[PDB]
Image (cartoon, coloured by chain):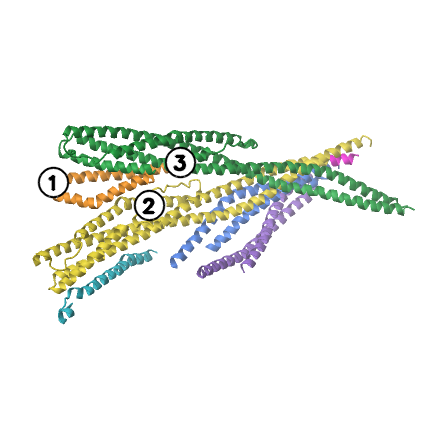
Chain colours: A orange, B purple, C green, D blue, E yellow, F cyan
């Protein structure tokens, strides 16, 4: 049982490390957009349609995944 | 065939044990013979005359014990060697039947 | 989740206390079981009389609060001062903080319930193992008894044989003695042999009766022990099945509780996010204020969902 | 190889039974030897019953020897039979696997 | 009730992660089995982490980009659309053609990823099966030994009873000898020396039998004890093997299903790649076409576009 | 066993893919075949139909 608990923690460590890399990537991606913006490389016209298209897809798909995980813990 | 084989295999183990018994009985007879012969020999070194028959009986017990161990070994080697042939046939038939039951399904 | 625990609770309440008083080896088992059952009962009464009701209250208050919390005026509603909007937001922020604290309180209650259930299930399992061991030992004894009972019937028949052989010897002796007596005219040796057969027949009948009365009387003691052990094992297997069922009920209730803990934890986090979204909007003047206020409006939907979710739990 | 294995496996359990036989036969020989030795000894105190006592002591000695020898063989044998059986099963599995890939 | 291909693999992945390493340290015959199992389990874990942390996410990304692309380019304008130069239409088509080419290359890339995943899963399932067979062999050998033990244990109880018999017979002989000796002694105090001798002899023999039996019994149970210990040890080892074996068997099934799920995903991407190539071919032949043959290839490309949009929805479901 | 594995990988990675391509090509072909009269209006030439 203790051995199994040790494995559960080892896996949770990997899961957490993964989450750390994900946030780190998002932080870096934001910095790149900021740098792209500041230099005049993009426009607040085009970057709006970019985030709006992601919201139409990816962002909505993540928001759903969040509500789903919230239920999976509750059993609701 | 499989039933006649299991019945024969049962009949074969009896001779196999009968040989195992003769081999052990021989080992004990020899062991006892040695103890007797040794006793008879030490009694001949005080009363030479009259502890010769004890030594003879001890040597005879040893001799018979060896004879039984030898005879049993010959029988055993042959008996397992008849048993082995029967078992091989049984396994072969079992495999064949299974294969048939496989393709049959 | 709640109904599943509510059912398991009332069910445990119905768990009757046992006296294995007849079984000497189950003395510790009975007391241990009784104590554990008593403790579980305490856990249930608390859960029923306080916990579930308190949880319902907090959720209801939260439900009413979010109900009032209309659509968030990220900019400021029509014909109001900036101070008026700030005051209303500050009031809402304070209320949310209180609600957050309440949510944390409910979680703690759930945590205690979880621990109580966990302890109950564990104690149940311990009783089951203790019982399983008793019947698994007792069934070694049972085999040695059946083997001894088989060995006893042989002596019982051996006595029955001696008794019958004696009856025949006497019967034959009488016929011989009578013949030998009529042949006396001498025929004294025949009469002697007949009397001897009669005498021996009586001796065998007497000796056998003594052995038989004693042999069945050893057999009786063995059979009594066998039956007693069989009954004890059955009783253990009876209470054992019941405890096993209770252990499962608790294991499920644990999952139900853990679920409720995660639900409250989510609501607490969602409130903290709305609070953070709110706070940063009060110390923001123009566009960044409307940004945090819109995010808080999304917070508000996330909390309203968490409410409906907890209500279902 | 499989035949030499079945022949060796037969020789392994054979010695195992041969020890089991000697241990039982040994126990009886000793039991009988003790009864005989005791009889022979009481007849030597009661006038020429030395040969009976000798035969009884010999039976006892042989009985003990068989019980001891069997125990030594058994303790040594038990580890060996398992190794042979493991190899037999492994070979059987390997042959099946080979027959499987072919099919 | 049935799961999507990805969820089936996602479940199998997290499940393999939970696979604990075992030590058959007590079992000498399972030494190689344990190490082999441990190694294979370790490798499978590596396959899962990759699948979970990289593969499934990368696949999702490529599909999403494809979904967005086809969304923008929903239907091919076979005819010269309203108020445009022929060059303007050609440029737009050429741009679409170039984008499709890039998307095709991306699709081939995803397929390669799937191929690697397939191989990784296949290897995992194979190693699992190998452990199962290795285990099955151990318990199937160990159960020959178990029978020889039960047969020997049966043969041992006979000597155990034979000793018990000698001990009792001795107790009775002594008891009877004492009664006889006492009788013979009282009859010698009237004028019965042979009776006393027989009584003393019966007593002597009774003691000898009780002593000899005790020696045999103590030794016989002590041979019986060794045999029983081995039997129990083998029984436990076999059970442990049958325990881990059931688990490995379940893991093997999980991998076999994941293999089917992966193969399905490979076929899906292959279809999307082919559908893109057809649209590209339909496009290319329309740029180097006169009036009517251009509209013909452009309409076929519009049908291509629907076939790709379907392939997208299909992959999304996988 | 290694060689057999090679045979399978080819069958799976290349045969199965080529088979899949075939269906797509067929799909594209029948797509155009319908598009033939779909484009060719009322009063197209016999030569125009023959060319298509």
Look at the image and tell me in which quarter the N terminus of chain F lies: bottom left
Position of F44 compared to E5: left or right? left
Q: Position of residue C113 (x, y in %)?
A: 38, 31
Marked residue chain, label 1: A
- The residue mark sitting in front, 3 or 2, is 3
What residue sits right under mark 3 in the picture?
Answer: C5
Cα–Cα span, label 1 and label 2: 41 Å
Q: Secondary structure at mark 2?
A: helix
Position of C212 compared to B27: left or right? right
Q: Which mark is residue A37?
A: 1
Residue B9: in sight, yes or no?
Answer: yes
In this view, the residue in front, A30 or C64, is C64
Magenta region, residue range: E192-199
Q: Position of residue C158 (x, y in %)?
A: 70, 43
Q: Position of residue B19 (x, y in %)?
A: 59, 51
Q: Quadrant of residue E170?
A: top right
């Amino acid at each position: 049982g203790y051995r199994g608990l040790q494995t559960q923690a080892q896996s949770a460590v990997t899961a957490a490390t993964q989450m750390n890399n994900a946030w780190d990537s998002l932080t870096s991606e934001l910095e790149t957009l900021n740098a792209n913006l500041r230099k005049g490389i993009i426009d607040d016209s085009f970057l709006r349609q970019l985030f709006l298209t992601a919201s139409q897809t990816s962002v909505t798909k993540v928001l759903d995944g969040t509500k789903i995980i919230k239920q999976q813990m509750a059993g609701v | 065939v499989l039933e006649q084989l299991n019945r024969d295999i049962d009949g074969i183990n009896a001779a196999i044990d009968g040989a195992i018994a003769g081999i052990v009985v021989g080992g004990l007879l020899v062991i006892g013979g040695a103890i007797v012969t040794a006793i008879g020999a030490v009694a001949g070194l005080v009363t030479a005359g009259t502890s010769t028959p004890v030594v003879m009986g001890g040597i005879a017990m040893m001799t018979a014990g060896a004879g039984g161990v030898i005879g049993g070994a010959i029988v055993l080697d042959k008996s397992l060697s008849a048993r082995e042939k029967l078992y091989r046939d049984r396994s072969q038939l079992n495999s064949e039947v299974l294969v048939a039951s496989q393709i049959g399904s | 989740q709640a109904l599943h625990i509510q059912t398991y609770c009332n069910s445990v309440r119905q768990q009757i206390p046992v006296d294995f008083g007849r079984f000497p080896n189950l003395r510790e088992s009975e007391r241990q079981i009784n104590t554990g059952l008593g403790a579980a009962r305490q856990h249930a009464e608390h859960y029923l009389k306080d916990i579930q009701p308190l949880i319902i209250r907090n959720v209801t208050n939260i439900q009413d609060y979010f109900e009032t919390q209309n659509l968030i005026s990220t900019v400021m509603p029509s014909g109001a001062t900036k101070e008026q909007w700030l005051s209303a937001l500050g009031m809402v922020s304070d209320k949310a903080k209180e609600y957050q604290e309440v949510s944390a309180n409910t979680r703690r209650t759930i945590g205690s319930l979880n621990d109580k259930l966990i302890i109950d299930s564990n104690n149940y399992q311990l009783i089951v193992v203790n019982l399983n061991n008793v019947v698994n030992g007792n069934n070694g004894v049972l085999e040695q008894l059946n083997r001894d009972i088989d060995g006893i019937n042989a002596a019982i028949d051996g006595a029955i044989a001696g008794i019958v052989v004696g009856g025949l010897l006497v019967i034959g002796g009488a016929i011989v003695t009578a013949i030998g007596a009529v042949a006396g005219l001498t025929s004294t040796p025949v009469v002697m042999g007949g009397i001897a057969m009669m005498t021996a027949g009586a001796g065998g009948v007497i000796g056998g009766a003594i052995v038989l009365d004693k042999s069945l009387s050893a057999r009786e003691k063995l059979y009594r022990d066998r039956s007693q052990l069989n009954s004890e094992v059955l009783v253990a297997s009876q209470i054992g099945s019941g405890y096993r069922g209770l252990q499962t009920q608790a294991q499920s209730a644990v999952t139900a509780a853990t679920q409720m803990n995660n639900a409250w934890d989510s609501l607490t986090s969602e409130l903290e996010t709305l609070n953070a979204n709110l706070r940063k909007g009060i110390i923001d003047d123009s566009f960044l204020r409307q940004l945090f206020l819109t995010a808080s409006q999304t917070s508000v939907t996330k909390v309203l969902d968490g409410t409906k979710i907890i209500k279902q739990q």
